[PDB]
Length: 229
Length: 229
Image (tube, rainbow over all chains, first blue to last red; front, side, top):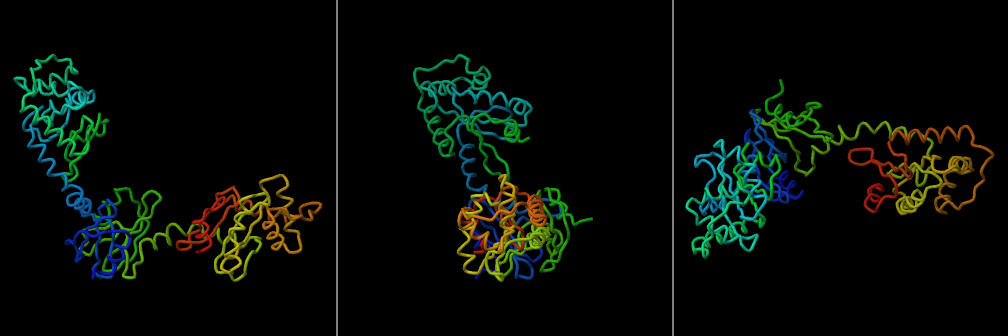
C-alpha cells in the first residue's frame, strides 16, 4: 500500500490527490485537509514523511506554488474565460497588463466609487477595467443599462456615466433590443454562476492565476491588490 | 552562514534555537514562530528545506514529540519539583501512578466539587490528589486551613471536610502555629508563582511531562485528562 509514514498522516485527516516528484530522492504527495491543500514528503530513508512546506535556495515556497497552481486555481479558469468571451466595455488601454472584470448596475453607488478609485491605475495604462453590465437593482436598471449599450460609443458613455455619478443624461430607446437583452441576461447568469449577486462584483487574477473576488467597495489594501500593485 | 533555504524560512518569522540530527541524511533545525515551536528539515540535495512535521512508520509525530519535550515542557519542571517538596496532604494510594496537585482553600465551592468529581479515580487507586492548602479567600480561611493541618490526621480531616461540603466541625486552636503559617505562606507563594490566584488551581503532567494547569471546576473533558484517562 502507501508508505506507512504517509498512511499515518492520512489518518490525521488528509485525503491524497496524487503523487509528484520532489528533490533529494524524496517523493511528494499532494493532498487536502478539509479545504486546505497540503504537501507531504517521504524522506530518503523511506521510513519517515514530513507534512509541511518546502522552500528552495531562492526562498520560494514551492509547496505554496504547487498548491495554488494545482488545487486552488484550476476550477475558476473556465469562468475567467467566459468573462473574456462576454460583451464587456473597455475602460483603459487595450494593452494594459492587468485585467479586471466588474459586474456593474447603473444604479449602484459603490460601482461608481470603485470606478473613481481605479482612475490612477487605468489612466497610467497599467490596468484595464472590463465592465459586464447587468440590470438587477432597480426597475429602470435594465433599460438604463441597455441605453448605455445602445449609445454610439458604449464604453465612453459608461465612463461618463460613472464619472458623473449617474447624472449623465441619456437617450433611452423605446425598448430594449434583443441583442442588448441577450447581453444583460447572459451577464447576469454568469455573475450568478460566480457566486455574488451584489454589485459591484469584481474579479481579478492573483496567486498562480487563482480567480479572485471582491464584492462591494474594496478597502485600500484590496484595491491595491486588485490593481496588481 | 545558514543554508539559503533555511535562511528563507527564518525571514518568514522564525527564530532558530538549535540544530539536531534527523533521518535520511537530513539536518534538523528547531525553532519558534511567535510562541509556537517549529521544526525545519534540510533536504539531501541541500538546496531545499521543509518546515513541517515529521512522522515515522509507527505513526508518531516526531516533530511534536521533540517540540513538547524541548520547548513547551522544560520551564515548568522545577515548579513540579517545588510542589513535590511542599507540605501536601495525600488523598489516594501513595503508589497511585497519576499525581495531581491542587491548591485549595477551605471556603471554596469548586474545590469541594472537584474533590467529589475525582472520587472514581482516587478510589480505584489510579490517581492520588496532593493538596497544598492556602488561606486566601475568607477572613477565617487561614485559621480553618491551619486547624485542618493541626488535626491528628490532617489528610483524613481534609477528606472529611471536602466530603461534607465544609460542614465538618473542627477544633480551631487559639492561634495559627508558626509551622502551619509557614506552610500556608509557602504554598500561597508557590501558587502565585504558578500564575493562578483562583482556587482550585489544579496541576498535572501531560504532553511529554509538560506542566498543565486547570483553574476552577474542570468540565468533563478536562477532568478526564487531568485524571490521566
